[PDB]
Amino acid sequence: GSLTEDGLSYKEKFVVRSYEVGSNKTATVETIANLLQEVGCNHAQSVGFSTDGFATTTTMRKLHLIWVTARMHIEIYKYPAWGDVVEIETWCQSEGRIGTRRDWILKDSVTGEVTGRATSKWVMMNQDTRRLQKVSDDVRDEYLVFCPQEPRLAFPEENNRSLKKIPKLEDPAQYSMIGLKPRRADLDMNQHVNNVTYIGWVLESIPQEIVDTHELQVITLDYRRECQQDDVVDSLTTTTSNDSQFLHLLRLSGDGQEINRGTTLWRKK
Amino acid sequence: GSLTEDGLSYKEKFVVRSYEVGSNKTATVETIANLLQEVGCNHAQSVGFSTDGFATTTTMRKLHLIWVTARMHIEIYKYPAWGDVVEIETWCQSEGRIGTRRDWILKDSVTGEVTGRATSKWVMMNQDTRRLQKVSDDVRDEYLVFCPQEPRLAFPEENNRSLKKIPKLEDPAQYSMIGLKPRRADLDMNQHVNNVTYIGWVLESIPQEIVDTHELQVITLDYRRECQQDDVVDSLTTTTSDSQFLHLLRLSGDGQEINRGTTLWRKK
Ligand SMILES: CN(C)C(=O)Cn1cccn1
Ligand SMILES: CN(C)C(=O)Cn1cccn1
Image 1 (cartoon, each protein chain N blue to C red):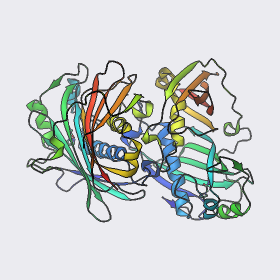
Image 2 (image 1 turned 45 degrees about the horizontal axis):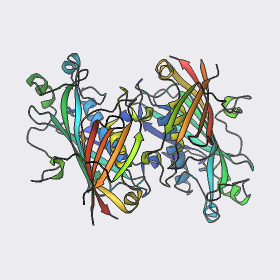
Image 3 (image 1 turned 90 degrees about the vertical axis):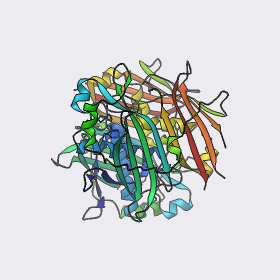
Image 4 (image 1 turned 60 degrees about the horizontal axis):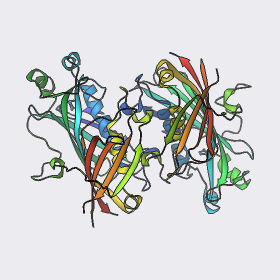
């Protein structure tokens, strides 16, 4: 991987692995999401930022401030086959005092065609108290020199899916997967649950017949609260719809405290 | 990756990924085991064998025969750091009518030193019926041309850990992790639970304090039965001692054994 010519974006190529593919012999959405986080991490490293998945400056580290994912939106047209090379280009953009946005474009290395796209919203938070705060000007300047100043949107469209409000699923859920717990492989270098695990947990309540006859086209996931290593999660899904649409809810098995909410769109193979 | 000059072994280089590392910023034993299976799969592909994790010939496919892991043994001296390049060399060897053995050597691409080694025992079985068979002679000829004929052992030593008999853990277990279930990410392209998930499940019953103050040096795992997609597993560990542990994976219900193993840990 490497920063592009203008130094305002980063590219990397990946060869799809045998254990990374599903029943269709193509990469899973979790393999895609892992690769987006890998290229994001390599972009933060190439310009001197922290690499613990929080992209902090030395100023943020002194104040115990971290960047956290508030929302992830992924759209896949073609899942890469096992052995195929996929090229991912990523860039970051300031969104004023709200926070930052990281975008991705996935391409087939052989054909050069866009096979997927992704966007994510990040907010600034105190690591310890979990309190959010708007971006200060002194912090803003530190990351602005690594971002394109004119807008560069992976999802340009006037009324696009990446910015839609997601409602809260009402009981009773149509489908559910109960008692999900993270194991050590689900944790990162800081012992926090990897954001990709929550995508997996959301998809666990999708019936196997949907997975067997459809392909996941869009996934929009909102992150409300972090699941701790010793927490237990319930995954809930209700059909909202040729295409199939679902409404999702991840909450703690006990008190029913919401950790995530999202939507998925599937297309018949 | 590519077959070596004599065509009897395969090499591949891997750059350690951010999500592949643990709290020490080095690769987990599950990341290592995934890379061993990846290079094994690429060696099977380069010589025309089956794509799935079964390395079958067209003759085995007609008789619904597959190669299955009976035992996995891994020894790590240094876990590669995030961003480091690790080179893995793998080869297969016939063991007469018992089955085959796949070996691995892990090296630091910068220093060239051996940072780890692995060995695995494979047996032939019917995929539907699950019955073992002692290699049909015609099958032997098909894979022998891809194996070194003289012995090439990753664990040469005469009384080494890779061939030790593992006993069955007796109740009550000292530690346990109950209600473990595989999710879709734990399955392979054929909807079977990946062998690396069982390594993860074994390690789940190791106390966090051991993981925090020690490094895993050796892991020997025996595979007795497959855990299905809708099965629920209990993970059991007892200290037998460096720290040594005895492990048992069994189904939560009837207590049917799926795996047994041992681990050896070194104080950091
Ligand atoms: C989400 N954030 C804060 C970033 O991605 C920061 N960044 C800009 C360029 C490289 N990293
Ligand atoms: C374990 N088996 C059956 C193999 O690894 C067969 N093989 C030899 C060379 C490439 N694949």
